[PDB]
Length: 103
Image: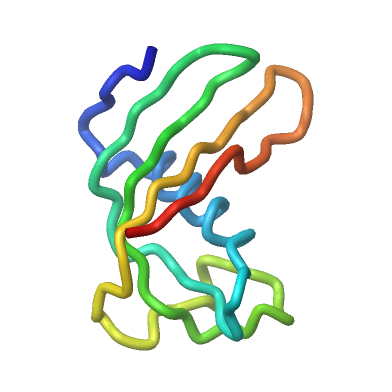
């Protein structure tokens, strides 16, 4: 099943959280961005799957721009919500977001 990973400050998990949030546009005029990764689990099945819990804030980038870590900066340090995404990285196909939910 899902195995807990620590420490959670690994740059890899940051990048995966940025990837997830880069595709989350429902009902938004601006992308959200990642403030902090709080929890990470992984599971190997049809590739590597990562379940990453993280805090988000509204970003400076409109959803009609390309999302980037360098350009989509938090408008404030206020936590908008805490979200959990699952990212699937197939062995030899394109990665994708399996699921995304927020409190």
